[PDB]
Amino acid sequence: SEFKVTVCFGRTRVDVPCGDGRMKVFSLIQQAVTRYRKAVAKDPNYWIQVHRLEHGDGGILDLDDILCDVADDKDRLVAVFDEQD
């Protein structure tokens, strides 16, 4: 099977299936962020400051480390960001 990680934006969980899995966190954040606003019924009107990601309580995720190295098949992640809603 392919890669798959869930990115919980504040109070919204969004699944992100990686075809190969070789996608840097930075690419995962941008992909999740876009899907987040599109999933929450939002649009490119309010600002969104994506701080960083975290596995939970022992596995932070920054925009540079590969997914296969950080994320894991069917793994959840807490996304901390800002939003002017």
Image (cartoon, rainbow, N blue to C red):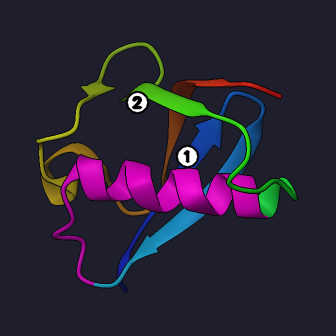
Which residue: 78% across, 31% down? 11
Query: For numbered disc 2, what is the local secondary structure?
Result: strand
Q: Is residue 64 left or right of residue 13?
A: left
Frontmost residue, 66 versus 75 = 66
Q: Main secondary structure of the magenta part?
A: helix
| Residue 55 versus residue 15 in the image, above or below | above
Q: Earlier in the sequence, mark 1 or mark 2?
A: 1
Displayed quadrant of residue 83: top right
Displayed quadrant of residue 59: top left
- Give the x, y percent position of residue 45: 73, 46
What number is the disc on residue 70? none
- Give the x, y percent position of residue 28: 36, 56
Magenta residues (range): 20-38
Quarter of the image where the N terminus is located: bottom left
What number is the disc on residue 53? 2
Q: Is residue 85 left or right of residue 77?
A: right
Q: Is residue 40 left or right of residue 15?
A: right
Task: Identify residue for label 1.
Answer: 7
Quarter of the image where the C terminus is located: top right
- Give the x, y percent position of residue 44: 68, 54
Q: Please, which residue is most extreme toward the front here? A: 45
**Type of amino acid at the residue the image marks with label 1:** Val
| Residue 17 versus residue 7 in the image, above or below | below
Tell whether position 23 is magenta: yes
Tell whether position 47 is magenta: no
Which residue: 21% across, 38% down? 63
- Give the x, y percent position of residue 19: 33, 84
Q: Please, which residue is most extreme toward the right here? A: 41
| Residue 12 versus residue 20 in the image, above or below | above
Whole-angstrom CA distance, mark 1 to mark 2, is 8 Å
Frontmost residue, 1 versus 79 = 79
